[PDB]
Image (tube, rainbow, N blue to C red):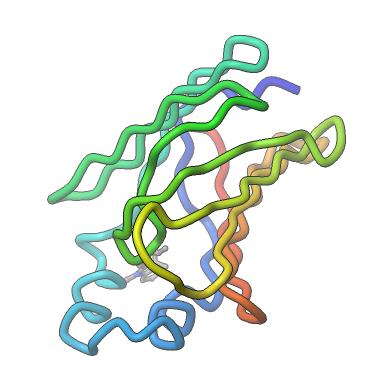
Amino acid sequence: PNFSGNWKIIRSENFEELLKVLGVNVMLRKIAVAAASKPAVEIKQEGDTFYIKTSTTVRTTEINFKVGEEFEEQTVDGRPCKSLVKWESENKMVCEQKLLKGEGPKTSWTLELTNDGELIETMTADDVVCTKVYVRE
Ligand SMILES: *C/C=C(C)/C=C/C=C1/N(C)c2ccccc2C1(C)C
């Protein structure tokens, strides 16, 4: 699959609830789910090597990884973690995360490219799943 593109969000389900069950305070949740925080996602894929930039009005997040090689990022609540992405199937990657410091809920994410070119993202903490869907600009 080729995940490359500039992706715009078209569906978001259970995001604030994920943050809430994770202990994020209401002032921060409000900011995090406001229109000003609507994420635009740029992906550059070169085979198994990925660059993913997520942009909001106030923040840029950039990750660089190759499938099967450990890399650093932050969990959805901003805690540094060691991440590892594997292909679950031809069109879907899954990332396992390990906190660099301390214990905490089991967090993960996935990205899947559909036949008609939609991008499905999931983010999980224990038994709570958030789903976002994007289309290319
Ligand atoms: C993951 C989702 C985030 C960070 C924010 C999304 C915010 C919104 N808002 C405020 C909104 C309003 C109408 C329709 C869609 C949305 C969206 C989910 C993008």
